[PDB]
Image (tube, rainbow, N blue to C red; front, side, top):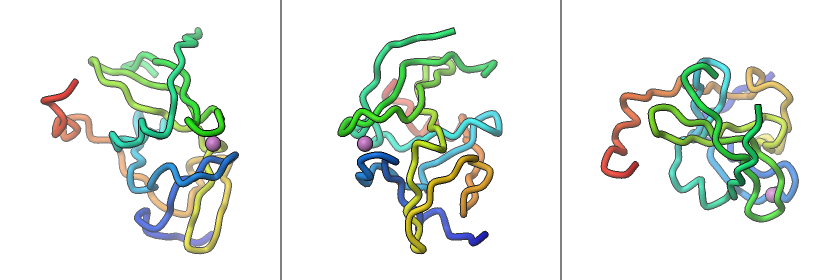
Amino acid sequence: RQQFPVEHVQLLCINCMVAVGHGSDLRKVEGTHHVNVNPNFSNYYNVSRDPVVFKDWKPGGVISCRNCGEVWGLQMIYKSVKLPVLKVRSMLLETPQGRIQAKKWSRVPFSVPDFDFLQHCAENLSD
Ligand SMILES: [Hg+2]
């Protein structure tokens, strides 16, 4: 399989395929959970409190495309902070090669850095 710089892969909604994110905004939490840490991201998803029943994070609401209503994943919270956790199969990866839908995050044509909580406090004033 190929390999691109994350900067070169854009996120689209598997369904409506609107440009919704950047692969460069992806982070790994607890190794596995893939969040997006770009604040401007919330402009693309609605949240809905369908709580349901991950050791340092409590799940928030279910997350879905503002534009077609596709479910993308669910919120996750830790020490008062809320991040959108993305399901791989809900994303269309727009590589310079074209568009590929994956079924495991561990198989995306780029590398996703671990999430840095401390440094995420570049966002202290808010929340
Ligand atoms: Hg959509």
